[PDB]
Amino acid sequence: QGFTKLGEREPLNDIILWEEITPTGHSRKEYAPVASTEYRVGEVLKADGSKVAAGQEAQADSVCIVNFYADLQLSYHGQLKVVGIYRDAELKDLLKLESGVDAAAVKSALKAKGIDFVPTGL
Amino acid sequence: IKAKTYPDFKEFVKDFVANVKAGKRYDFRKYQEAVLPLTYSSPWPESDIPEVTDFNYTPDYTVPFSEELLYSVGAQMRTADFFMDLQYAIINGKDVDTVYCEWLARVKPFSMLNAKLKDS
Amino acid sequence: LTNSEKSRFFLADLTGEVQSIPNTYGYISGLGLFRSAPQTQTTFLMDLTDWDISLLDAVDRTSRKAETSAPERVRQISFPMMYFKEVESITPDEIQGVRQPGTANELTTEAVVRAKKLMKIRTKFDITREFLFMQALKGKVIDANGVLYADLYKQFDVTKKTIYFDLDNPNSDIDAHIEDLRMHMEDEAKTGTVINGEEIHIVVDRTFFSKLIKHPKIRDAYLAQQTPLAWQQITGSLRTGGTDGVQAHMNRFYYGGVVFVQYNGKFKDKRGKTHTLVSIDGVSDTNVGVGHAFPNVAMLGEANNIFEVAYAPCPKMGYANTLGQELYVFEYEKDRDEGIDFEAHSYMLPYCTRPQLLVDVRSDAE
Amino acid sequence: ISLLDAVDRTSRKAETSAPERVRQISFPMMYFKEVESITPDEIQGVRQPGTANELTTEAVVRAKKLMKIRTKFDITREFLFMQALKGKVIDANGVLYADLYKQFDVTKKTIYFDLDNPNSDIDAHIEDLRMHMEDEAKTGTVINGEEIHIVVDRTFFSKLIKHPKIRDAYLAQQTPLAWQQITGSLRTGGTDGVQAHMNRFYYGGVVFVQ
Amino acid sequence: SKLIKHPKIRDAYLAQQTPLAWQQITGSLRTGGTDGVQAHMNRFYYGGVVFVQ
Amino acid sequence: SKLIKHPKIRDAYLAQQTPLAWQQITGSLRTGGTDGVQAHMNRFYYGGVVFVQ
Amino acid sequence: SKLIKHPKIRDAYLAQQTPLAWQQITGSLRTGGTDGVQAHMNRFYYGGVVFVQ
């Protein structure tokens, strides 16, 4: 065949638009990565550190802003943790949701927690 | 066929074939310029086309080129000859489906007219 | 020289980089129709005065009786304006570690990212301006979302004029519809001067142009001609003029004293729905052609210009009560060296002071 | 890119733009070689053809063999160039080396002129060709659709010349000076290796070259 | 409109190859003075007479 | 009237491009010749003869 | 004779206003040459080729 496709760049951490900037990490939480689970920028995480599944969007906790690879225990910056924005901040509307996940419900939960989403163009 | 009865060529040839199927035959190769209006969007015919009773036309070539074409696509022939060759096809048992006149530009002496033929 | 595939120890070559810039259309913007009218306040008013005339009725002499004329009518209207704001941010974590596309092992800097972000913002504002200008040409200024901002026909108390060309019917009178469109501008201009209806712009879409240039009447008329114009229009390039945003030459056709230009401009919004510039809100039958006819700049003269666009200052800390601008760009840095913030503002409204002259054109029959 | 939406000035709301996408692509390339040898046995005692008693020279044989090698490489390079212009870069032996359409993840475009249908629409297909040239090229600059080499074979050329839509239009075109396209020679320019002038036809602003 | 549309006049003029013939058919027409609202008035030439709209 | 509109004569004069054919196809047919009532009398040229109404 | 009689060849010159078309449709067609018995050989032009009888 004549078409080797080397691959495609993972999304960059550009969804952050404004956050409460503090000496420590305000609106930023560290999660112990769930075993054999791959994280990317924009996925919505639960309190334990797992992606939000269908029927439980009411407990959405944060938006992952790192690219974690499950197969080598590390991330894209070589940090062995998963970081997501949980407290008040504003993000681009680029969310990765699992099958059957109601976007309005998780949006409302994050808005109640203080996170606002700016409508991003196509 | 009375003069200027049909508002275009498409509706003119629709009842020209029907008349031929009914046993009516026409011949106007000698006074061709007096019966064909210029441009296919003009009312047809320019003057009344008389009937004939002694239509004995045997062309020197095979009039049905294929089983579904009167001439090879792109063949140019005298306009009066097109109607005779068309009349030869209906007489021998070929039926006319569509007469190709959509993008044609000339009606006088030579025109690139064609017909799609069918059995029965 | 970059790492080869399959192996981290052998090398390959990185020849270059191919880019796919989206298509952008700027025909209406480049036409120069909408003269710029910078504004200081957030709203601008307008006075509308008109009078009417009637025929005298014969009245006998001995019984000394006469007639009188009604006085003038003066009104006033106001206009709101649309505000567009767009924010973009640069962060160190989209620069650190990330590799510059098209290069082997050199890294992206802040300058290239900032330049590309600013270019994208300016292009977005340009296409938004073009879409707004086209909507104003349609007679109704509808925002991309769909909210109504200024309905010129209700504001000036006029009714929209549409002409059905009926291009499908081979017996249709193209000349009659062209004459109707030509005389409508002269009749409804009501500027008090002498109008030349032949100086108009007719902008149509692909289907209308295709049906118009393939009509039996038009083609049979131009085929029986021995002028260079007919030779070019029949067997020749139908792409005179142009300098469109995408194509170098737009399709145009000369039949009467008017010309028909085919404009293919279209954009998409955030929701994903496409916004064809030459369209009628409601019609979508696919097989019907639509067009928009609006007066030329040199029809009512420069003294009476009907296409203007307003601009008012952004609500910043030092721009109040100043003349408006095409676009504002502001530089704001995040505290603690955490990034850079961008803001772009533009407060505008395109409008037409004689909406009656904006005539719609269709290809089907009424 | 997308379209901005109007925003209330006092509320200070705003819009945002999505980021770009980056992909990578690799290509293999084809290697071929040719070997020739000169021995003092094809220049020893053999007469130069066309001469009575003139012996051949080592320099003559060297130049002849080098010229043959160079022209063989020239013709195979021309064949490879033509293959690349068709998208799929395959060898004379038929082994595929690079499939650009699968590589760049695009779909091959094909315009079916239907030259055997007398009421076909040649202008519509030419306009489709121009539109595909202009829209699909996403260079981001102003593009001209009438800047294409339309290289065809003898069958397509012959069927296109005598189509009723084109031939009738040119025949009705009196005093065009381009009667040459109907009556005069069509060998009106260009040259390949063996033919002094190549067939070319002008219609709709584009040139069809056989 | 009906006069300039008529097939007899149109076809009689469609053959003449003279600037006048090129102007009456698929041309601007509108060859005349003003009446008060339009710059030029429709004028058709045929048979030695002039039809003025 | 019957003569000037005959298909043979009309299509023989339509096909030729001379000022005469334009004159007596689309132009005025009055040419010259007084009548005592008419200022110009209808004249038509087809062959070497001229027809006068 | 069969070549010049063919409808395509005749049509290609009938609708042409070049003096060559006029000479080849109506004119002598015995352009030039001398085969020793006739004063002018008859030739035909249909492109870059010349047909000589």
Image (cartoon, coloured by chain):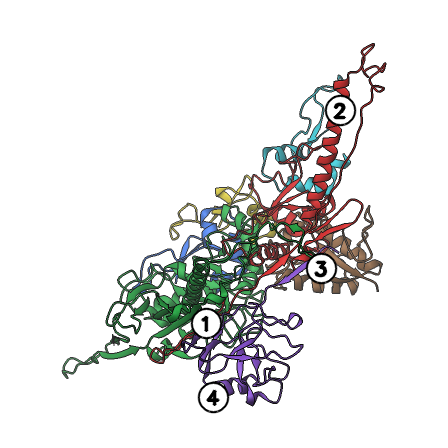
Chain colours: A purple, B brown, C green, D red, E blue, F yellow, G cyan
Which residue is tagged 4? A112
Discs 1, 2: same chain: yes
Q: How would you rate the neighbour count of disc 3 (Cα within 10 Å): few for under 14, some for 14-19, many for 20 or more?
A: many
User: Can you tell which mark lies on residue C71?
Assistant: none
| In front of the other: C96 or C141 | C96
Q: Report the Cα–Cα distance between label 1 and label 2.
A: 69 Å
Q: Report the Cα–Cα distance between label 3 and label 1.
A: 59 Å
Q: Report the Cα–Cα distance between label 2 and label 3.
A: 62 Å
Which residue is tagged 1? D16
Which residue is tagged 2? D64
Q: Report the Cα–Cα distance between label 4 and label 3.
A: 73 Å
Which residue is tagged 3? B99
The disc, 1 or 2, on the residue closer to the chain's N-terminal end is 1
Q: Of tags 2 and 3, which is closer to the observer?
A: 2
- On the image, the x and y values in percent for residue A65 come to 53, 74
Discs 3, 1: same chain: no
Residue C211 seen from this side? yes
Q: How would you rate the neighbour count of disc 4 (Cα within 10 Å): few for under 14, some for 14-19, many for 20 or more?
A: few
Q: Chain of mark 4?
A: A
Discs 4, 2: same chain: no
- On the image, the x and y values in percent for residue C287 come to 59, 70
- On the image, the x and y values in percent for residue B81 come to 73, 50
Three-letter residue code for mark 3: Val
Discs 1, 4: same chain: no
Three-letter residue code for mark 4: Ala
Task: State which quadrant residue B93 falls in.
Answer: bottom right
Residue G33 appears left or right of C203: right
Q: Chain of mark 2?
A: D
Does dot 2 land on a helix, a strand or a loop? Answer: helix
Q: Chain of mark 1?
A: D
Q: Chain of mark 3?
A: B
Q: Up-down: is D27 above or below C310? A: above
